Length: 117
Ligand SMILES: Cc1cc2nc3c(=O)[nH]c(=O)nc-3n(C[C@H](O)[C@H](O)[C@H](O)CO)c2cc1C
Ligand SMILES: [Cl-]
Ligand SMILES: [Cl-]
Ligand SMILES: [Co+2]
Image 1 (tube, rainbow, N blue to C red):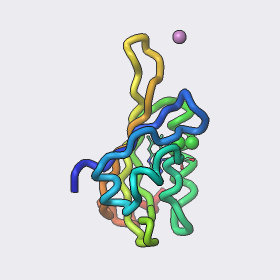
Image 2: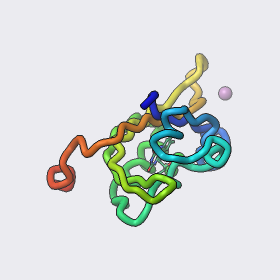
Image 3: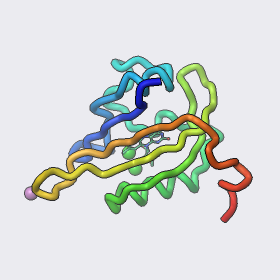
Image 4: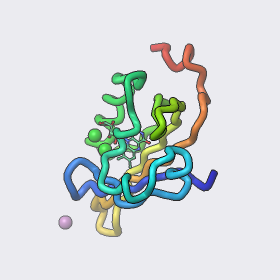
């Protein structure tokens, strides 16, 4: 698929998605128009590990890049493993301007290893 990513605006409440790539639409099965303005957690669901969610939340607060692997859901309810790479984007003034999150679909690290401390 074309590279899956979204861009959020941390200068607006709770990181709304301001851009979603064609690859993200293809991976997730959502339309662009229905994605825009959402927080990226809309892809989560019952099987998503809340400990991994908390890691993300801490990295966003700290404006620190992070990679995690977590369960996400397509619009039709299909589960997929998402290796999510989140990167803060700063402007020339050093000010946070965007986050970008790139999704790679796959159980790259087997669940039994991911689950160790
Ligand atoms: C740019 C960006 C992209 C994100 N993409 C995803 C994603 O693909 N899947 C997901 O489960 N959470 C994603 N999140 C994390 C989610 O929005 C939220 O920050 C965490 O669930 C903590 O509440 C993303 C966050 C940002 C800032
Ligand atoms: Cl967010
Ligand atoms: Cl958050
Ligand atoms: Co300033």
